[PDB]
Length: 122
Ligand SMILES: CCOc1cc(N2CCC(O)CC2)ccc1Nc1ncc2c(n1)N(C)c1ccccc1C(=O)N2C
Image 1 (spheres, rainbow, N blue to C red):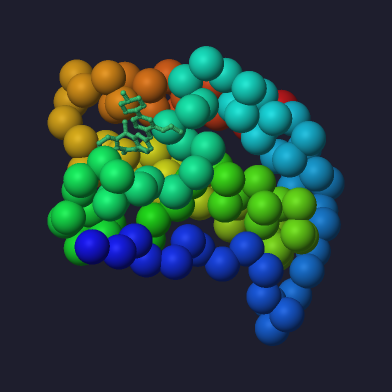
Image 2: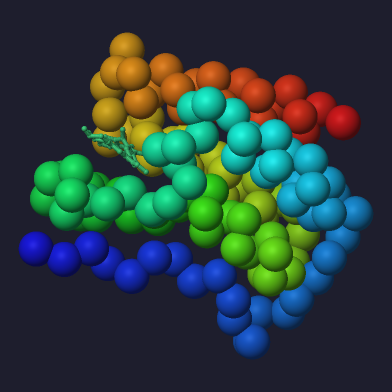
């Protein structure tokens, strides 16, 4: 019947930071993934209503997507780069937990994860 609210992208109790690694994650790592041909499923929250996934938000306890990560980065939401990296890992992990080995969406996530890891190697 209804999707939960997307994850928060701003929080005035949460100190704003921008570190040099966070600056790289936005301007290089997120930008590279965002423009990839496999990005489209991950550019917004999972729409469990439209995809007809009544159990998604029961199983996936920390939903995450790159639209949220982009906004977090743009809003200086993260305290350091490790917390941003954790969000990306959560995003890939959610897709692997909900879906099945060999599903196209899974194979897309694995390719983006590999790319992500290659880019965070600078
Ligand atoms: C922006 C446009 O988004 C979509 C368009 C279409 N279609 C449908 C069929 C029409 O004919 C044309 C368009 C289908 C899916 C998406 N979006 C989308 N968002 C998130 C997920 C995802 N798909 N996949 C594939 C998953 C499917 C099942 C369970 C989980 C997921 C999943 O883990 N993620 C990340």
